[PDB]
Image: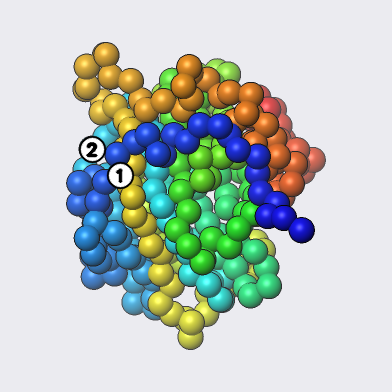
Amino acid sequence: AYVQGPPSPGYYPSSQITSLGFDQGYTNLWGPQHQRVDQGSLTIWLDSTSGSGFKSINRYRSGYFGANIKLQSGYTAGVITSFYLSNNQDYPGKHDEIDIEFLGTIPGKPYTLQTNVFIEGSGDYNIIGREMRIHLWFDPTQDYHNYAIYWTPSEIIFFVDDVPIRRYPRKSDATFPLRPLWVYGSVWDASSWATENGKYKADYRYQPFVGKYEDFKLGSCTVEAASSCNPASVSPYGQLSQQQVAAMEWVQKNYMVYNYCDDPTRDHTLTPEC
Protein backbone atom coordinates (compact mmCIF):
# COMPACT_ATOMS: atom_id res chain seq x y z
CA ALA A 1 0.00 0.00 0.00
CA TYR A 2 1.09 3.58 -0.72
CA VAL A 3 -0.16 7.11 -0.05
CA GLN A 4 -2.95 7.71 -2.85
CA GLY A 5 -3.06 11.44 -3.50
CA PRO A 6 -3.28 13.69 -6.54
CA PRO A 7 -0.45 13.68 -9.04
CA SER A 8 2.03 16.53 -8.60
CA PRO A 9 0.85 19.70 -10.38
CA GLY A 10 4.57 20.45 -10.99
CA TYR A 11 4.35 24.08 -9.86
CA TYR A 12 3.40 25.49 -6.43
CA PRO A 13 1.88 29.00 -6.68
CA SER A 14 1.45 29.34 -2.89
CA SER A 15 5.20 28.80 -2.30
CA GLN A 16 6.13 31.69 -4.62
CA ILE A 17 3.99 34.24 -2.78
CA THR A 18 5.00 35.89 0.51
CA SER A 19 3.00 34.69 3.53
CA LEU A 20 1.41 37.54 5.50
CA GLY A 21 0.08 37.89 9.02
CA PHE A 22 -3.63 38.64 9.38
CA ASP A 23 -3.06 42.30 10.34
CA GLN A 24 -1.02 42.99 7.18
CA GLY A 25 -4.01 42.15 4.96
CA TYR A 26 -7.25 42.11 6.96
CA THR A 27 -9.35 43.51 9.81
CA ASN A 28 -12.33 42.16 11.76
CA LEU A 29 -15.63 42.90 10.04
CA TRP A 30 -18.11 41.56 12.62
CA GLY A 31 -18.15 39.63 15.88
CA PRO A 32 -14.79 41.11 17.00
CA GLN A 33 -14.69 39.17 20.31
CA HIS A 34 -14.91 35.89 18.36
CA GLN A 35 -11.60 36.63 16.61
CA ARG A 36 -8.04 36.49 17.96
CA VAL A 37 -4.67 36.92 16.28
CA ASP A 38 -1.55 35.24 17.63
CA GLN A 39 1.70 36.12 15.82
CA GLY A 40 -0.26 36.73 12.58
CA SER A 41 -2.34 33.52 12.83
CA LEU A 42 -6.11 33.93 13.05
CA THR A 43 -8.58 31.99 15.20
CA ILE A 44 -12.29 32.72 14.73
CA TRP A 45 -15.33 30.97 16.15
CA LEU A 46 -19.09 30.50 16.27
CA ASP A 47 -21.10 29.86 19.39
CA SER A 48 -24.72 30.49 20.36
CA THR A 49 -23.96 34.20 20.98
CA SER A 50 -22.22 35.04 17.68
CA GLY A 51 -20.18 34.00 14.67
CA SER A 52 -17.35 36.13 13.24
CA GLY A 53 -16.14 37.48 9.93
CA PHE A 54 -13.19 39.43 8.56
CA LYS A 55 -12.55 41.56 5.48
CA SER A 56 -9.50 42.61 3.47
CA ILE A 57 -8.06 46.09 4.04
CA ASN A 58 -7.87 46.58 0.25
CA ARG A 59 -10.25 46.17 -2.70
CA TYR A 60 -8.89 44.23 -5.72
CA ARG A 61 -9.32 43.98 -9.49
CA SER A 62 -7.45 40.65 -9.82
CA GLY A 63 -5.19 38.27 -7.92
CA TYR A 64 -4.26 35.11 -6.09
CA PHE A 65 -6.02 35.09 -2.71
CA GLY A 66 -5.12 32.28 -0.35
CA ALA A 67 -4.73 31.04 3.17
CA ASN A 68 -3.83 27.96 5.13
CA ILE A 69 -6.99 26.86 6.92
CA LYS A 70 -7.71 24.22 9.55
CA LEU A 71 -11.24 23.01 10.34
CA GLN A 72 -12.83 21.61 13.49
CA SER A 73 -13.40 17.89 14.01
CA GLY A 74 -16.48 16.13 15.37
CA TYR A 75 -20.04 17.37 15.04
CA THR A 76 -20.03 20.61 13.04
CA ALA A 77 -23.32 20.23 11.16
CA GLY A 78 -24.94 23.45 9.95
CA VAL A 79 -21.79 25.56 10.31
CA ILE A 80 -19.90 27.01 7.38
CA THR A 81 -16.27 28.14 7.46
CA SER A 82 -15.63 30.40 4.47
CA PHE A 83 -13.01 32.12 2.37
CA TYR A 84 -14.50 34.25 -0.39
CA LEU A 85 -14.52 37.34 -2.58
CA SER A 86 -17.54 39.64 -2.77
CA ASN A 87 -18.66 43.18 -3.56
CA ASN A 88 -22.16 43.15 -2.01
CA GLN A 89 -21.09 46.06 0.21
CA ASP A 90 -20.39 48.06 -3.00
CA TYR A 91 -23.27 46.82 -5.21
CA PRO A 92 -25.90 45.87 -2.64
CA GLY A 93 -28.60 43.57 -4.06
CA LYS A 94 -26.85 42.90 -7.39
CA HIS A 95 -23.35 41.76 -6.54
CA ASP A 96 -20.57 39.40 -7.67
CA GLU A 97 -19.06 36.71 -5.46
CA ILE A 98 -16.53 33.86 -5.64
CA ASP A 99 -16.82 31.32 -2.81
CA ILE A 100 -14.94 28.63 -1.00
CA GLU A 101 -17.22 27.20 1.71
CA PHE A 102 -16.44 24.26 4.00
CA LEU A 103 -19.81 22.71 4.78
CA GLY A 104 -19.95 21.39 8.35
CA THR A 105 -20.47 17.70 8.88
CA ILE A 106 -21.34 14.89 11.26
CA PRO A 107 -18.93 12.23 12.48
CA GLY A 108 -18.44 9.56 9.79
CA LYS A 109 -19.27 11.86 6.87
CA PRO A 110 -16.37 13.75 5.31
CA TYR A 111 -16.38 17.54 4.99
CA THR A 112 -17.61 18.95 1.70
CA LEU A 113 -15.80 21.86 0.08
CA GLN A 114 -18.21 23.90 -2.06
CA THR A 115 -17.00 26.34 -4.71
CA ASN A 116 -19.45 28.84 -6.19
CA VAL A 117 -19.58 31.88 -8.48
CA PHE A 118 -22.23 34.62 -8.51
CA ILE A 119 -22.41 37.41 -11.09
CA GLU A 120 -24.51 40.58 -11.30
CA GLY A 121 -27.28 39.48 -8.94
CA SER A 122 -27.35 35.71 -9.55
CA GLY A 123 -26.72 35.31 -5.79
CA ASP A 124 -29.01 38.04 -4.42
CA TYR A 125 -32.70 37.14 -4.65
CA ASN A 126 -33.66 34.64 -7.34
CA ILE A 127 -30.57 32.55 -6.81
CA ILE A 128 -28.89 30.77 -9.71
CA GLY A 129 -26.29 28.43 -8.27
CA ARG A 130 -22.99 27.60 -9.93
CA GLU A 131 -21.89 25.08 -7.30
CA MET A 132 -19.28 22.37 -7.53
CA ARG A 133 -18.74 20.22 -4.46
CA ILE A 134 -15.92 17.85 -3.64
CA HIS A 135 -14.69 15.80 -0.73
CA LEU A 136 -11.01 16.09 0.15
CA TRP A 137 -8.25 13.50 -0.11
CA PHE A 138 -7.09 14.34 3.42
CA ASP A 139 -8.62 15.18 6.78
CA PRO A 140 -8.99 18.97 6.76
CA THR A 141 -9.26 18.99 10.58
CA GLN A 142 -5.87 17.42 11.36
CA ASP A 143 -3.63 20.10 9.90
CA TYR A 144 -3.67 23.39 8.03
CA HIS A 145 -4.05 23.05 4.27
CA ASN A 146 -3.67 25.70 1.56
CA TYR A 147 -6.79 27.00 -0.18
CA ALA A 148 -6.98 29.75 -2.79
CA ILE A 149 -9.10 31.63 -5.29
CA TYR A 150 -7.23 32.88 -8.34
CA TRP A 151 -9.20 35.52 -10.27
CA THR A 152 -8.21 37.47 -13.40
CA PRO A 153 -10.17 38.98 -16.32
CA SER A 154 -9.80 35.62 -18.18
CA GLU A 155 -10.44 32.92 -15.55
CA ILE A 156 -11.16 31.87 -12.00
CA ILE A 157 -9.22 28.89 -10.60
CA PHE A 158 -9.82 27.27 -7.21
CA PHE A 159 -6.80 25.59 -5.52
CA VAL A 160 -6.27 23.08 -2.69
CA ASP A 161 -2.63 22.48 -1.67
CA ASP A 162 -1.63 24.04 -5.01
CA VAL A 163 -3.81 21.48 -6.85
CA PRO A 164 -6.43 23.14 -9.03
CA ILE A 165 -9.87 21.67 -8.27
CA ARG A 166 -11.92 23.83 -10.66
CA ARG A 167 -11.46 26.29 -13.48
CA TYR A 168 -14.20 28.74 -14.43
CA PRO A 169 -13.17 30.41 -17.70
CA ARG A 170 -14.58 33.71 -18.91
CA LYS A 171 -17.04 32.74 -21.65
CA SER A 172 -19.22 35.86 -21.61
CA ASP A 173 -19.37 39.15 -19.69
CA ALA A 174 -22.79 38.27 -18.26
CA THR A 175 -21.47 35.02 -16.69
CA PHE A 176 -18.10 36.27 -15.33
CA PRO A 177 -17.16 38.55 -12.38
CA LEU A 178 -15.71 41.71 -13.92
CA ARG A 179 -15.90 44.22 -11.08
CA PRO A 180 -13.69 44.85 -8.05
CA LEU A 181 -13.93 42.50 -5.08
CA TRP A 182 -12.92 42.44 -1.41
CA VAL A 183 -11.69 39.31 0.36
CA TYR A 184 -13.67 37.85 3.29
CA GLY A 185 -13.80 34.89 5.65
CA SER A 186 -16.31 33.86 8.26
CA VAL A 187 -17.74 31.15 10.46
CA TRP A 188 -21.53 31.17 10.64
CA ASP A 189 -24.67 29.12 11.21
CA ALA A 190 -26.10 27.97 7.88
CA SER A 191 -28.25 25.19 9.45
CA SER A 192 -30.98 25.70 6.81
CA TRP A 193 -28.95 24.03 4.04
CA ALA A 194 -25.28 23.41 4.92
CA THR A 195 -25.28 19.77 5.96
CA GLU A 196 -27.17 17.30 3.77
CA ASN A 197 -29.43 20.16 2.63
CA GLY A 198 -30.41 20.93 6.25
CA LYS A 199 -31.02 17.35 7.49
CA TYR A 200 -28.46 17.90 10.27
CA LYS A 201 -28.48 21.27 12.00
CA ALA A 202 -26.21 23.17 14.38
CA ASP A 203 -26.09 21.72 17.88
CA TYR A 204 -24.55 24.24 20.22
CA ARG A 205 -23.76 21.59 22.85
CA TYR A 206 -20.63 21.13 20.69
CA GLN A 207 -19.74 24.86 20.68
CA PRO A 208 -17.52 26.68 19.97
CA PHE A 209 -17.02 25.95 16.27
CA VAL A 210 -13.56 27.15 15.40
CA GLY A 211 -11.88 28.10 12.12
CA LYS A 212 -8.14 28.72 11.94
CA TYR A 213 -6.42 30.71 9.17
CA GLU A 214 -2.70 31.53 8.61
CA ASP A 215 -0.09 32.16 5.93
CA PHE A 216 -2.29 34.60 4.08
CA LYS A 217 -1.35 35.16 0.48
CA LEU A 218 -2.31 38.25 -1.52
CA GLY A 219 -0.54 38.06 -4.90
CA SER A 220 -2.92 40.65 -6.18
CA CYS A 221 -3.63 43.96 -7.89
CA THR A 222 -5.59 46.69 -6.12
CA VAL A 223 -8.23 48.52 -8.16
CA GLU A 224 -6.11 51.59 -8.87
CA ALA A 225 -2.68 49.89 -9.08
CA ALA A 226 -0.55 50.66 -12.15
CA SER A 227 -1.61 48.86 -15.33
CA SER A 228 1.76 47.11 -15.14
CA CYS A 229 0.54 45.25 -12.02
CA ASN A 230 -0.02 41.59 -12.72
CA PRO A 231 -1.50 38.98 -10.39
CA ALA A 232 0.77 36.25 -9.01
CA SER A 233 1.62 33.59 -11.56
CA VAL A 234 -0.49 30.43 -11.62
CA SER A 235 2.17 28.70 -13.78
CA PRO A 236 5.73 29.46 -14.99
CA TYR A 237 4.64 30.41 -18.52
CA GLY A 238 0.97 31.38 -18.00
CA GLN A 239 -2.21 29.30 -18.27
CA LEU A 240 -2.69 25.97 -16.50
CA SER A 241 -0.05 23.43 -17.50
CA GLN A 242 -0.86 19.91 -18.60
CA GLN A 243 0.36 18.67 -15.20
CA GLN A 244 -2.00 21.10 -13.43
CA VAL A 245 -4.91 20.05 -15.65
CA ALA A 246 -4.14 16.36 -15.02
CA ALA A 247 -4.22 16.91 -11.22
CA MET A 248 -7.54 18.79 -11.57
CA GLU A 249 -9.01 15.99 -13.70
CA TRP A 250 -7.91 13.48 -11.02
CA VAL A 251 -9.64 15.49 -8.27
CA GLN A 252 -12.84 15.81 -10.27
CA LYS A 253 -12.89 12.14 -11.32
CA ASN A 254 -12.30 10.85 -7.80
CA TYR A 255 -13.71 13.49 -5.40
CA MET A 256 -16.39 15.58 -7.10
CA VAL A 257 -19.87 14.89 -5.68
CA TYR A 258 -21.89 17.71 -7.27
CA ASN A 259 -21.64 19.88 -10.36
CA TYR A 260 -24.49 22.25 -11.23
CA CYS A 261 -23.84 21.78 -14.97
CA ASP A 262 -24.46 18.03 -14.60
CA ASP A 263 -27.64 18.30 -12.50
CA PRO A 264 -30.74 17.34 -14.56
CA THR A 265 -33.05 19.24 -12.19
CA ARG A 266 -31.23 22.50 -13.02
CA ASP A 267 -32.33 24.71 -15.90
CA HIS A 268 -29.02 25.07 -17.75
CA THR A 269 -30.30 27.87 -20.02
CA LEU A 270 -29.76 30.12 -16.97
CA THR A 271 -26.09 29.07 -16.93
CA PRO A 272 -25.01 29.22 -20.59
CA GLU A 273 -21.30 28.90 -19.70
CA CYS A 274 -21.93 25.17 -19.06
Q: Earlier in the sequence, mark 1 or mark 2?
A: 1
Q: Are marks 1 and 2 in contact (CB under 8 Å)?
A: no
Q: Tell me if 182 is positioned left or right of 78 in this view.
A: left
> Looking at the picture, does residue 67 appear above or below residue 239?
below
Near-viewer residue (271 or 240): 240
Amino acid tagged 1 = Ser
Residue 60 in picture, x, y percent from top left: 30, 31
Tell me which corner region of the image, top left, top right, bottom left or bottom right, holds residue 42.
bottom left
Q: Nearer the viewer, mark 1 or mark 2?
A: 1
Dot label at residue 19: 1
Q: Can you give x and y, in whole percent of width and height, for residue 135 in the image?
A: 65, 54
Kind of residue sitting beneath label 2: Asn
- The residue identified by callout 2 is 58
Mark 1, Cα crowd under 10 Å, few <14 / some 14-19 / many 20+, is some
Q: Position of residue 128 (x, y in %)?
A: 59, 39
Rendered-image quadrant of the N terminus:
bottom right
Please name the residue shown 26% across and 46% down the image: 20
Q: Which image quarter: residue 170?
A: top right
